[PDB]
Every structure is written in C-alpha cells, then in structure tokens.
Image (cartoon, rainbow, N blue to C red; front, side, top):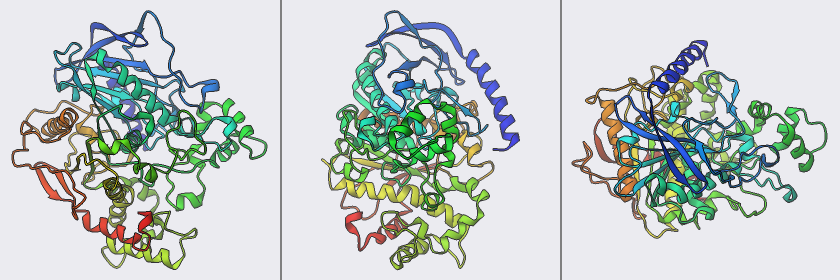
Length: 566
C-alpha cells in the first residue's frame, strides 16, 4: 500500500482517536452477565444519536501458552465490576495499510451495543461476524461502528475470533489435540455466551440473527452447519459468501511443517516436534510468515490462504467440521431457519489491485483451466476433460478474441461467489423443511462515502460495486462522515439497516415502512424456480431476475457428466 495512503491512514487514525474521546460521555452503566458485572459507557454518533457500548467482554480464556492452537475454554468468572469501556486488541494479523504485524493473542472478546438498556419489550439480537479471509479483521469501532444500527431498536454484537495459523493450524496426530478450526470454535463459544446473556442487555434470546460478510459469510454459514450450535440462533444472512466457496475451506495439515521450517525449525516432519516448535515461537513471527507458506502449485490452483477452515482429521468433543461442507449441508439444522443471501453487482471488481501487480493472470482465461473447480480438474490442468470444462468457462466470460481484465474480474465474481451460491441453494433445496431463502443483489455505487477495503483493493476512482462496498452502509468507519438526510447515501443506510432489522425481527425482509419498497413483492426462492429472483438494490429497489443466471448455468454445465459432485 502506497506511502500516501499510509500517511493518510495515519492521520485518520489520529482523527478517529480524538473523535472517539469527544463522542464519549460520563454516563457509565452496569450490566449483569453470567460471568460477573460489566461496566459499559454511553457514546454519541455523528448523527446526534446515542448508544450504550460494552466492549472487551471475554467469552473465552485467553488462548495463550499451552492453549495456543487449541479449542477455546470458558473464561474465569469474577466478582466485582469489569471495565468494558474500552476495546481490546485484535487477533494477531498483518496490517494491510502498514504491512506490520499487529494485535495480540489475547483477542477473544465481543462487543455489545444498544440505544436502550431497559427496553419495554425484549429486542432482536443481531450478531456480526467480520470477514477478512480468516486472516485479518476486528470488532473495533473504527472499522465496525454500530452508529447506523443503533437508530433501530435492536441489540447489536460484534465478535472477534482467532485468525490465521493461530486460529486454524491443523495436525493429523490425534494425541496432540490440534484438530483444527480453533477460530470457528471461538465463534461457537461466543454464540453460547450470546444465547445465555443477551437478555441482560434487553435482547430476546429466542430471536437471534447471525450475519457476516466474505469470510464472515462463510463463518455464518459454518455456524448454520455445525451440530455444535443447533437451535442457538434463528435467522442467518450470508453476505457475499458461504462455506462451499472454494476459498472457504482447505486441507492444511501438511502446511504446519512448512510454516515451522520458515520460522527456523530444525528437525523432521513429525507433528509432535512441529507443534512444540510452533508453541514456543513468537506469535508475530508466525503471522508474518504465513504469506510464504503456499507453494506455487497451490497458488496456481487458486488456493488463497494457507490456513483456514478444514475437515478435522479426527472427532473431538468441540469438533466443528467433521465432514466436507457440502456433506454437512445435507444434515444442517441451519437449513430450516429463515435465510437471506446476496452478492454485490460486480464482486470480482475487487481484484483490480492484484491484477495490476500480476498482468499475466489475465492470460489464464485463454483456456480457463485454472478456474475449473478443483474437484473436477486434473493435477497439471492438462487433461482433455479439463480443457473442455475450461472451455465452458471461457465461453461464459470472454467477450472477444482476446480476454480482458474485465472478463477476468467478471469470472472471479462467479468463481468465488455466484457459483458457490448457486450450488448451495440447489443442495439446500434437497434437504430442507422449506423455510424461505431470500436473495438480494447490492447494486448501489457511491464514492462520497467509503470504507477502508477500498484502500486495499485500490478502489479509488473506480466505478462499479465491488465486494465489501456494502459494509459502508451498515457500519460506521473512521473514513466515514455525516451525510445529509436527503442524500442517496443516507437513504441507503436507512434502507439497508432497515431491511436487515426487518429480517432479523420477523424472518421476512419486506416492509412498506422502508422508503422505496412500495411496489416491491419480494418472494423467496422455490426449488421449482429455473431462474432466481432477487431484490436489486440501487437508487431504486426493484425485483428482478438474477442477471448472472445464464453464466451460473454455464458453470453448472461443467458437472454434466459429474452430477454427483454438484
């Protein structure tokens, strides 16, 4: 990230600190939790509203020392008042602006926000799980501020969980008790805390919505798949992702060795000796080195991250993912709660940054074999069958004689988001009670209000609605500002927070109390539907046929002779 964006960020970081102080009040308050009393503080927003803020609530034991790489344990109770007027540190990770490692192994906290601590009726509980490819992210308010949500009468909760190798290291040796998915197991324990305590904040434990975006969407879906969380929450919103996206799980059991070797491990490839080294290593040295773990073969085959969600190699008491996600859908309790899913209108437009450093990637569309789903393609991607599936992809996205960068980013919309969404719906249809699933397409483009991911994806002065462009209208961030109440940006904030709170409360996303939904008839998807219908969210709210349907079906055609793999 460029020196100018670095200094610009440094200055906004300084601005945000002074804004956070100014927006604090002296009105502290105390709530009960099952672990002891917590002191929160009331804060202000730039729209002159206010909310009670409880930050730094522990839902697990600090995962340090011997607890590193392991399943989370329940925190120790305390008798007194715990200071929750300040945020805790984020999971150890690389800062995308600075490129330096930041954060701490002590990161298993959650935040609880609400405009009213003593409501007259118990309120819908909204739980946000952040994305960041399972390697970055945080519940800090400079990125995920509840300022918009607290206009509505809900309780909003933002959790943290362990990222990267510290969250997702996986070893085969059953004696070592590092089956993997510690970071997902962090999410589970946070849920159990939310189930059992949200009532003390005015929240209704029988009306909980979990939602997330990117890796947060995949996490939300994982929380809907696992038996570990059955009945814990009641609605799910999958924003630009799910657990059968090709980036959302990986078999990383061999990669521990590689990471230890990068970090200075001298010795042989056996799990026990690898673990012992990794247990004593400095957390920052490990995270710094994660970028180098993937081989060139893996990157070629589109493996995006070294460590993430995995099929655990043996079953433990806290096991989250015992079979592949596609298999788990077939027995998922989550299949039978109201679900909303959606994507932006140009998801893949996100990859512009990466494309600029790697022009050569656009030549991959000449045959498109590297984008054939892994489970269908051969090792070298050279089999005649593979060139045949590749051809079906190329016909779908390459528009002229020679492939373009826009062909590429369009393909990525489908490779990373639409096609996995299509596979999940169809699969889900075969194994569900028949609860509704609603689709949205976020198609609202503005450069007047933005969020920090635009800095990362080099999205300055780029038209189109990229992956993460919609977070801007849900959460406050330190790049935001007060928007006029008549502006298109403000109206979209109302519409987005409105629909989500509408869905959270009733399990039905439609309301005529939302400006612009007067002629909206928003129907759920049926298994009989050959074509998906979605609410398209731009300046106007319009029900349409999903525009990406034709390409979606083309991708499906790759499974013609392999329908059991679909």
